[PDB]
Amino acid sequence: PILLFLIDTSASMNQRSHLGTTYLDTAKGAVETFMKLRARDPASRGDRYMLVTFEEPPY
Amino acid sequence: PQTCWFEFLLEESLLEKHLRKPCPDPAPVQLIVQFLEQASKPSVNEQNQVQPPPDNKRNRILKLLALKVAAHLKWDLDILEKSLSVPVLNMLLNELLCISKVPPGTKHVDMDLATLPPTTAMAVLLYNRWAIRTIVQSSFPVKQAKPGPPQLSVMNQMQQEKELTENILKVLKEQAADSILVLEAALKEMQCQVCYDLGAAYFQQGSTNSAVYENAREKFFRTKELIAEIGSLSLHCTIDEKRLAGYCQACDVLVPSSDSTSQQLTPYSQVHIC
Amino acid sequence: KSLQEQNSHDAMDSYYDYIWDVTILEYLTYLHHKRGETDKRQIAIKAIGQTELNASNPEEVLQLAAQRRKKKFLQAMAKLYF
Amino acid sequence: DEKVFTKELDQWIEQLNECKQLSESQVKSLCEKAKEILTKESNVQEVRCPVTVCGDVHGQFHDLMELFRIGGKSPDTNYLFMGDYVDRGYYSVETVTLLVALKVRYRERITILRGNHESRQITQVYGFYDECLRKYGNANVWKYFTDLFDYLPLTALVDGQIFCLHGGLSPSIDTLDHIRALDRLQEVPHEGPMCDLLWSDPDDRGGWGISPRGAGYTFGQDISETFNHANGLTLVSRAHQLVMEGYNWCHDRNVVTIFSAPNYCYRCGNQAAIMELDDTLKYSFLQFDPAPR
Amino acid sequence: HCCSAPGGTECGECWGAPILSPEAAKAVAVTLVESVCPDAAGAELAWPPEEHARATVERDLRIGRRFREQPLLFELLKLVAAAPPALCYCSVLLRGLLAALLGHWEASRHPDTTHSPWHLEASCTLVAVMAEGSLLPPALGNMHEVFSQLAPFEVRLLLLSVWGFLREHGPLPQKFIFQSERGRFIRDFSREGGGEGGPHLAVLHSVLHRNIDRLGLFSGRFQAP
Amino acid sequence: MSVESEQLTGVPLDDSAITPMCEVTGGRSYSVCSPRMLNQCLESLVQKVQSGVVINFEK
Ligand SMILES: [Mn+2]
Ligand SMILES: [Mn+2]
């Protein structure tokens, strides 16, 4: 199925957890883990992945 | 040349030849470790059921070979303790007591040392001294080696042997006083060693109660007198004079025996008393 | 409405340390990036990234931090005038 | 005593120059001595210029001999090899023996960093243990060299400007004081600041990200820039990623990836590079391709 | 002069020194805290467990560096120790210094401790200042005398025991009982349940008894707590 | 670092202006506080990846 990822891009996420890493980078890592896990499903081939950012279009 | 326990299991004089070698490879303590490990290996039944190793003829041969090596070493508690683990020492001492024909389970204090044969007497004395020294070393704070990343295979054995060591330590603590009573009677070179062990045990115990310090002081003074009497001819007594001197200073801080000149005149102890 | 105008007279950069609300700093970062002022955009990013404030603490530390920054700001502000 | 031992060490050096590994007893005596000679260096073992930085080796003895041919003999040109010199090579034992022998012979004409591959776990499953067992039969030398590998420093500082470390930066670490406070007498843990230092790497991303290696992280342009500002460093030098030019700049002249093991695994065929800084901190570069065999 | 309230009572005949102002000590402690480390993440006056220091190492290291650079802070700390209650407020600085010393002592391969000169003095001063500040029984106050003649791990485990004891007995403004006879607030030991070191004094005794080789003369101090 | 040990066996719902929209469109918005339960949420998403029709049922 269609997979879309709307990632917040405002400065707010630039905070850092006790891991010393930003919320944005944690989000990217979580997305990567998600795609890794989904790859285990044979139906993965039918998946199309999308990214969207909070910035004003066309970007 | 490397010779494992199988050679000595098959042939007995091989042990004699190895101990006669000026450089026995492996070292005798390593031989003890290997033999007792083989003896203590648990028995797995066909149903994958773990059970204590049956005491077969091979097991008895291993045990008596280890005991022969220990006798050749002359039962140097320093060497055995430093080079061998607490469970190993405990089981080896128990086996030595058993081969001494001592009825297992009988409390040591119940038997008169003089009545027993000299070998059994020294065996019981060595067992009690080892128990006291084990308690003292357990009380000693020991630096912990830097932990590596988890190794699930080795940590199993490490934790298992640590638990067994803790159980042995608590067992020894439960009977520590009885060992003191036995050693007190046994005191009537080996006498100096026993007296020093008793003094150290008394000092450790009196860490809480100051009364035991007087007994420790008397023991340490008798130990130094024994050192003076024996002289340099100590072939089995190996005790540092500096530690007992410190013990005597600490106890004299408690008991003033007059004779200020003979006793410390340092401004330090003088300010202590002042 | 106040941060928007360009006629500041109050050492606009050095004061970013005292501000302790994440949202206004988000506004500041957006404004600086849009107007093309990276030397201050980085300062704003650092101020946000500071661990003291995260908008998710048990608030025991957040209130203390806000109190401390208030003290520092009002102390400097009092030093400036008179 | 010391004099006769020095001459004896000279014989070991010349012999190792002939690809002939030492005896097991000699290896034991070498490791024992090396413990006392490495115990005295903190994590950031500062080294004064001039210097010749050398990247990854992976124990390729012919390549190392050609590298000596190029840069110069060890007593003359000071060297700062960076890690990973024990694995994926058919002469790894000889290479590591030569490196440690040079270090012990000369305390300050050379300095060796600790790469990711110098640990107990990695060597067992990446050849070095097998090589040692095949050559010396037993594992006594293996348990000597693996023990030695912990006493190595972690990073080097050249005239307070260049920062040489194998892997790269790490989200936990921020300042040289933290590196100095880190304790090294520990087999590289699988997760932690020490772990990442040996598995970090550059990337054109920004922020951070999990490394595909499974350990450490991946830093971005802005991270390196911020770290350099934080501590006045002007250039970081790492060598963990295989390259082609041998030396490659990244993060707009902030991190130099060096690699001094040409034709990686005998098949990549990549050239190899070596950097050298003169007394006035005047960097240069040399390149080479493995000697005929 | 500034902190000491004149009082005017002329304590004693001519010997009794005037007591210092707890409020002045409070002000000094707070301003010193803000000067050194404006951080307040670990402002909970209750001491967290040892593992918690692992996350706070970086701040701990910067505090340690600042101290090494500026020795005057030790004298200010002694001045604050003069007043009983100010230390409870000056809790984060001490936690940071202790974390730094613990971390440093671990990475000490030298068999002797005196090899690292400054750290030894810093540890001694820390322990003595705590003793004078009365967050430790005098038994543990004697602790600092023996640091010189000890292996590194010995001192590290010893300071870990100190950490444990203080964790049990969290410094708080309460338990500093005011005395009408003398303004100086008193913390009455043995009324906190734990009282003396107990388990921790056992560790101390075990250390000194293991190191009777050169500590016999010093052993006469601790006696029986 | 969260000294609290998270014994929760589920993913508690979050309180944000998005949450009503998430419920309206048929999704369970997730709040996270540690990497472990983040991974729990992640695997929850992977399992939730399916094909269906969202219908409003009414008695
Ligand atoms: Mn490599
Ligand atoms: Mn590497």
Image (cartoon, coloured by chain):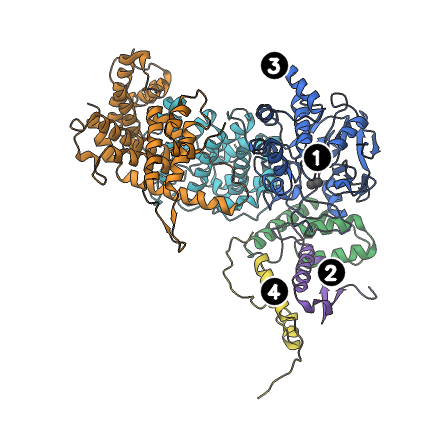
Chain colours: A purple, B orange, C green, D blue, E cyan, F yellow
Element under disc 2: loop
| Front residue of E218 and D57 | D57
Residue lying at 42% horizontally and 37% vertically, measured from the top left: E134
**Residue at mark 2:** A9
**Residue at mark 4:** F43
Spatial CA span between label 3 and label 1: 30 Å
Q: Mark 3 — on which chain does it sit?
A: D
- Are the residues under badges 4 and 3 in a single subunit? no
Q: Is residue D139 left or right of residue C77?
A: left
* Quadrant housing residue E200: top left
Q: Relative to D26, does residue D250 appear above or below in the rendering? A: below
Question: Which amino acid type is marked by label 4?
Answer: Glu
Numbered mark located on residue D2 in the image: 3
Spatial CA span between label 2 and label 4: 24 Å
Q: Mark 2 — on which chain does it sit?
A: A
Discs 2/3, front: 3
Q: Relative to D23, does residue D121 appear above or below in the rendering? A: below
* Quadrant housing residue F46: bottom right
Q: Are marks 4 and 3 in contact (CB under 8 Å)?
A: no
The tag earlier along the polypeptide, 3 or 1, is: 3
Discs 4/1, front: 1
